[PDB]
Image: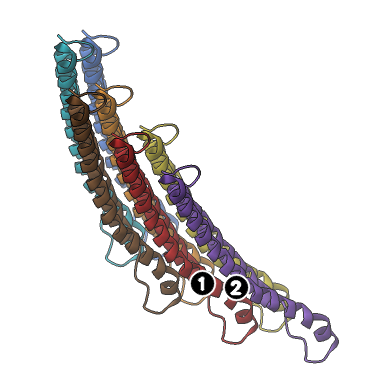
Chain colours: A purple, B red, C brown, D orange, E cyan, F yellow, G blue
Amino acid sequence: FGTNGFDIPTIAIALLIVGVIIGLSGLILSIFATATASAISNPSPGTLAYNLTHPLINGMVSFFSFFPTLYVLLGVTGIVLIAAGIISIIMEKF
Amino acid sequence: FGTNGFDIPTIAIALLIVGVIIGLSGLILSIFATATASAISNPSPGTLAYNLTHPLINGMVSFFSFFPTLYVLLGVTGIVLIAAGIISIIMEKF
Amino acid sequence: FGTNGFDIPTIAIALLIVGVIIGLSGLILSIFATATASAISNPSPGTLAYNLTHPLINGMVSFFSFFPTLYVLLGVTGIVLIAAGIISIIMEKF
Amino acid sequence: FGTNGFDIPTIAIALLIVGVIIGLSGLILSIFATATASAISNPSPGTLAYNLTHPLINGMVSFFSFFPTLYVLLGVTGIVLIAAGIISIIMEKF
Amino acid sequence: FGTNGFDIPTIAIALLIVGVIIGLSGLILSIFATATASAISNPSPGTLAYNLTHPLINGMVSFFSFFPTLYVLLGVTGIVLIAAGIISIIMEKF
Amino acid sequence: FGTNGFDIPTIAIALLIVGVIIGLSGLILSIFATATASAISNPSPGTLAYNLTHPLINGMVSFFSFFPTLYVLLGVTGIVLIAAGIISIIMEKF
Amino acid sequence: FGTNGFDIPTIAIALLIVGVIIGLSGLILSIFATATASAISNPSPGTLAYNLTHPLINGMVSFFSFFPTLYVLLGVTGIVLIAAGIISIIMEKF
C-alpha cells in the first residue's frame, strides 16, 4: 500500500517500535534513578564531601533537565516524515 | 479489477492490515503504559528523587500527546491515495 | 462477452470479491475491537495512567471515524470504472 | 477437497486438536492451582514472611489475569486463517 | 463425471468426510467438557483459589463461544467451492 | 495448522508449559521463603548482629519486590508474539 | 477384517483385556484398602502419634480422590482411537 517506499503498515509498526522503546527507556531510567537517589547521602552543608560531590549531582540534574526538549524533537520528527510521504504521493500519483 | 496497479480488493485488504495493526499497537501501548504507571512511584514534592525523575515523565506525557496528530495524518493519507487512483482511472479509461 | 478487456462476468466476480473482502474486514475489526474495549480499563480521571493512556484512545476514535469516508470512496470508484467501460464499448462498437 | 493446501477436513481436525489441547491445559492449570492454594499459608499481615511472600502471589495473580486476553487472540486467529482460505479459493477458482 | 477436477462423487464423499469428522469432534469435545466440569470445583467467592482460577474458566468460556462462528465459516466455504465448480463447467463446456 | 512456523496447537502447549513452570516456581519460592523466615531470628535493635544482618534482609526484600514487574513483562511478551503471528498470516495469506 | 491395522476383532479383545484388567485392579485395591483401614488405629486428637500419622492418611485420601479422573481419561481414550480408525477407513476405502 504505497508508491515507492511509503507504506502505511510499515509506518504503523515503526510508530509501534518507537513508542515501546521510549516507554522502556523511561521505565529503566526511573527505576535506576530511584537506586541512585537511595545510594547517595547528604553528608553536611560545608564539609569536604559536600565540596567533593555537589557538582556531580548538579550535572545530573542539568542533563535530566535537558532530556525533555530532546523528546520533543523526537516527537516532531515523525510529522515531518509523514508529511513528506504525503507530498511525495501527491507529486506523481497524478 | 483495475487498470495498472489500482486494485480495489488489494486496497480493501490494505485497509484491513492497517486497521488491525493500529488496533494491536494501541492495545500493546495501553497495556505497557499500565505497567509503567504501576512501576513508578511518587517519592516527594521537592526531594532529590523528584528532581531526578520529573522531567522523564514530562517527556513521556509530551510524546504521548504528540501521537494523536500522527494518527490523524495516517488517517488522511489514504484518502489522498484513493483519490489519486480514481483520477488515474478517469484519465485514460476514456 | 466484451470487446477488449471489459467482461461483464469478470466484473461480476470482481464485485463478488470486493464485497466478501469488505464483509470479512468489518467482521474482523468488530471482533478485535470488542477485545480491545474489554482489555483497557478506566483508571481514574486525573491520575498518571489517565494522562498516559487518553491520547491513544483518542487517536483510535479518530482513525475509526476516518474509515467511513474511505469506504464511501471505495464504493464510488466502481461506478467510474463501469461507466468508462460502457463509454469504451460505445466508442468503437459503431 | 480443496485447491492447494486448504482442506476442510484438515481444518476440522485442526480445530479438534486445538480445542482438546486448550481443554487439557485449563484442566491441568486448575488442578495445579488448587494444590498451590493449599500449599501456601497466610503467616501474618506485617511480619517478615509476609514481606517475603506477598509480591510472589501478586505476580501470580497478574499473570493469570493476563491469560484471558491471550486466549482471546488465539480464538480470533482461526477466523483470519479460514477467511484467507476462502479468499484464496475465490481468487483462482474462477 | 466431470471435466478437469470437478467430480460430483468425489464432492459427495468429501461432504461425507467433513460431516463425520465434525460429528466426532463435537462428540469428543462434549464428552471431555463434561469431565472438565466435574473436575473443577467452586472454592469460594473471594478466597485465594478463586483469584487463582477464575480467569482460566473465563478464557475457556470465551474460546468455546468463539467456536460457533468458525463452524459457520466452515459451512459457507463449501458453497463457494461448488459454485466455482459449476462456473468452471459452464465456461468451457460450451 | 499454520503457514510457516505459526502453529496454534504449538502455541497452546507453549502457554501450557509457561503457565505450569511459573506455578512451580512460585510454589518453590514460597516454600523456601517460609524456611528462610523461620531460620533467621531478630537478635536486637542496635547490637552487633543487627548491624551484621539487616542489609541482607533489606536486599532480600528489594529483589523480591523487583520480581512482580518482571512477571508483568513476561506476561506482556506473549501478546506481542501472537500479534506478530496474526500479522504474518495476514500478509501473505492473501 | 480391516485395511492396514484396524481389526474389529482385535479391538474387541483389546476392550476385553482393558475391562478385565480394570476390574481386577479395582478388586485388589478395595481388598487391600480394607486391610489398611483395619490396620491403622486412631490414637488421640492432639497427641504425638496424631501429628506423626495424620498427613499420611491425608495424602492417601488425596491420591485416591485423584484416581477417578484418571479412569475417566482412560475411558475417553478409546473413543478417539476408534474414531481415528473409522476416519482412516473412510479416507482410502473410496
| F68 relative position to E82: left or right | right
Count all numbered tags in the image, as a single digit.
2
Chain letter, disc 1 residue: B
User: SS of the residue at dot 2?
Assistant: helix
Image coordinates of residue G18 in percent, x first then y, are 26, 24
> Residue B62 got which mark?
1
Residue at (28% x, 41% y) in the render: D79
Q: Is residue D39 above or below residue F41?
A: above
Toward the viewer: F74 or E94?
A: E94
**Amino acid, disc 2:** Pro
> Chain for mark 2?
A
In the displayed structure image, the side of residue F54 where residue G57 appears, left or right = left
Label 2 close to label 1 by CB (< 8 Å): yes
**Closer-to-camera residue (D52/E82):** E82
The residue lying at 57 percent from left, 64 percent from top is A74
- Residue E14 visible in the displayed image: yes
Residue G84: horizontal and vertical position, in percent? 26, 22
Name the kind of residue labelled 1 in the image: Ser
Farthest-out residue, bottom: A46
Q: Is residue F31 left or right of residue E49?
A: right
- Residue on which the image places disc 2: A68
Does B47 sit above or below residue E62?
Answer: below
Q: Residue furthest front?
A: C94
**Residue located 14% across and 20% down the image:** E86
Question: Which secondary structure lies at badge 1?
Answer: helix
The picture places residue F65, in percent across and down from the top left corner, at 55, 67
User: How dense is the environment of label 2, judged by Cα within 10 Å: few (below 14), some, or many (20 and up)?
Assistant: many
| C12 is higher (above) or lower (below) than D61 | above
| Residue F91 found in image quarter | top left
Q: Quadrant of residue G54?
A: bottom left
